[PDB]
Length: 133
Image (tube, rainbow, N blue to C red; front, side, top):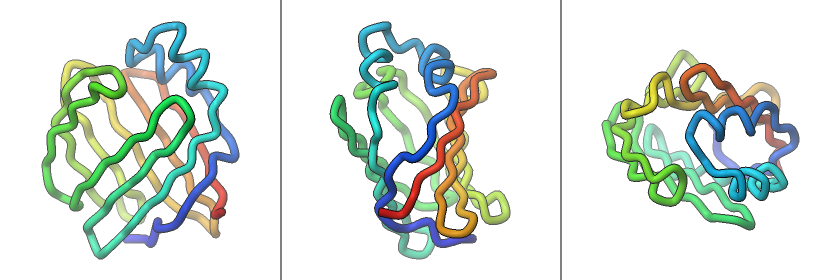
């Protein structure tokens, strides 16, 4: 495991548009979303996590415990329901989201004081890095 806690600000994004296309987000929302610099707040208590994703266009919140399946109604995103599970891929916090979309999920990890994030959905992978605020 690794400590991923803190308030993070998006430093670099990469292929976020491909990621969103794969989700089926419309033109209007994608144009606005790609212009955002969302903040990520990670509260970590042992294997208990609460991750806040704050941005202009929308605020997001996910609360989970590692190894505990939980449904994710993304009616604030792609409106598609998913059955999620987060596990420790050695020091990388990886989530598998089973649902309509295939090979959808995300992975967080930290190297130095920089937070990395990969968000994928059936072929598209959006890489992002954040800096401790």
